Amino acid sequence: MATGQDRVVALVDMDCFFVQVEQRQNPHLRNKPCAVVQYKSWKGGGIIAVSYEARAFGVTRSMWADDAKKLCPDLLLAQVRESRGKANLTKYREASVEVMEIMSRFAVIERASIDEAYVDLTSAVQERLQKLQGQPISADLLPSTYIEGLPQGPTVQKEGMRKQGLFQWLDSLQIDNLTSPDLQLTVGAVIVEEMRAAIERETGFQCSAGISHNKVLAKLACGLNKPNRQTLVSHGSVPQLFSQMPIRKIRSLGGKLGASVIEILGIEYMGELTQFTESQLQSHFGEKNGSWLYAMCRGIEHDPVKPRQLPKTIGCSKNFPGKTALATREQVQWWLLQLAQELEERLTKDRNDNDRVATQLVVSIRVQGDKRLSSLRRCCALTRYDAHKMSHDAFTVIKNCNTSGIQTEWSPPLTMLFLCATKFSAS
DNA sequence: ATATGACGCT
DNA sequence: AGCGTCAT
Ligand SMILES: Nc1ccn([C@H]2C[C@H](O)[C@@H](COP(=O)(O)NP(=O)(O)OP(=O)(O)O)O2)c(=O)n1
Ligand SMILES: [Mg+2]
Ligand SMILES: [Mg+2]
């Protein structure tokens, strides 16, 4: 066993991100139950982000604003900007950039969503460990850090607990030895406190972090103490932590695979996987998955933090649910044009900022009926950032999908259009 | 009826 | 190349 204690990895995720972006801009919304919403026309718009004050009333994502007002009569709402007849997320992308640029200053980051990134702090920890000369680590360096699983053994409020675990941890801490993994996580954590102070100081956004030995544990830990707090999950904390951790809560196990592990194995919790041999697990779920479950239920995972702060694709989509589905060749050309146009603006920007060009265009459509996300995908060359050309070509490579013998109509009505630029390349 | 992005498998 | 899974 290489006790997967070779790296220090952190995941930083912003608290109710879209809400914070709106609240920084409109101070009236601060410290109040509020949500960000998309498309006012239908039931007040669907909710995409909720403040913690509003979560306390039960408001969630996937909820009509109308319905959320019932749980929470005083809920304030901000709408997503809308442009060319669709949601426009530029404000959130720009806020995201602010945050990525700051984290990038500390370390090598992997952009994992619009509001989170992974950081590999192995080197910064090592470096910081040479320049602190065996000087102890004070609790005052860790003003927002929880140590998962402490306190234990021999104040009933939350900050009281926080501190006692932190004190126990630190008093435990094995400081004259620099190869200690726990000490490294600690130093990593001091670093992420700094990171997190820089982010708030420079953008006014609060976030949470997890600090551990790998991406999966870091991500899990991030959630344990949201909002505005960070959590160190040490290797030794894993058996107790996983012993009642529902399987679905681990990254990549929230879907069918996780369900099949539960069903086939007849278990509920991560820790229960330890009782199987790697071979048994590979027989059930394949070589890479068995291997991966066998390691992961023991807290070990080697997926690296990828040095990638820029998306691999840029894309645009719109659903036409139910009656609104597109059923004329005019509707299809016109929305393709609407989408091509945003994509053109986002591409030109991208090229200026990041010295690269996309080279392939991916057209996706959904049809009325077909089960889920995409029904059909077709590719063509992306050679000019021209919305009219991208539109034209996108149509070209999907027109044959139209079963309508009549020239004007489109059948079946399309319930989704998606354009995506991909295959980027230095420029 | 609530816009996006990464990546594996064939 | 085109489809399927998993995620925010
Ligand atoms: N299904 C989803 C999930 C998130 N998002 C957007 C809005 C979120 O504010 C933002 C960040 O995602 P998120 O981390 O899952 N949630 P959020 O940051 O809002 O709240 P917490 O992380 O504090 O729980 O992505 C979305 O548009 N659709
Ligand atoms: Mg978040
Ligand atoms: Mg997130």
Image (tube, coloured by chain):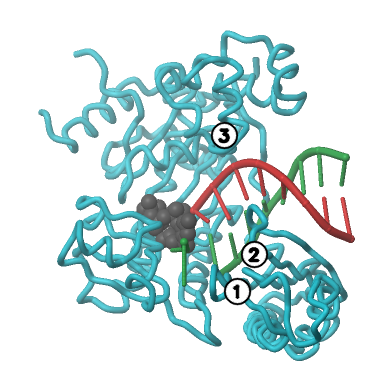
Chain colours: A cyan, B green, C red
Front: mark 3 or 1:
1
Q: What residue sits 24% from the left and 34% below the top? A: A162
Residue A286 placed where, x, y %?
Answer: 75, 24
Q: How far apart are marks 2 and 3 (CA)?
A: 30 Å
Q: Identify whether A388 is placed above or below A420.
A: below
Q: Compare residues A96 and A322 and report the one nearer the observer.
A: A322
Q: Which quarter of the image is occupied by the N terminus of chain A?
A: top right
- Residue drawn at x 32%, y 27% is A170
For residue A53, say whether it is visible. Answer: yes
Seen at 59% across and 34% down, the residue is: A7
Residue A98's place in the image compared with A275, above or below, is below
Residue occupied by mark 1: A325
| Residue A37, placed above or below residue A337 | above
Position in image of residue A110 (x %, y %): 61, 53
Which of discs 2 and 3 lies nearer the camera? The answer is 2
CB under 8 Å between callouts 2 and 1?
A: yes
Q: Residues within 10 Å of mark 3 (few under 14, many from 20)?
A: some
Within 8 Å of ligand 1, the CB of disc 2? no
Between the C-alphas of marks 2 and 1, the distance is: 7 Å
Residue B9 vs residue A292, the one in the foreground: B9
Instruction: Give the quadrant of the C terminus of chain A.
Output: bottom right
Disc number for residue A38: none
Q: Mark 3 points at which residue?
A: A253
Which chain does tag 3 point to? A
Measured as percent of width and height from the top left, residue A372 is found at: 63, 54
Give the side of residue A240 with respect to residue A296, left or right. left
Mark 3 falls on what kind of element? loop
Between residue A133 and residue A186, name the one nearer to us: A186
Going by the numbered disc 1, the residue's amino acid type is: Ala
Q: Is residue A383 left or right of residue A145?
A: right
* Residue under pointer 2: A368
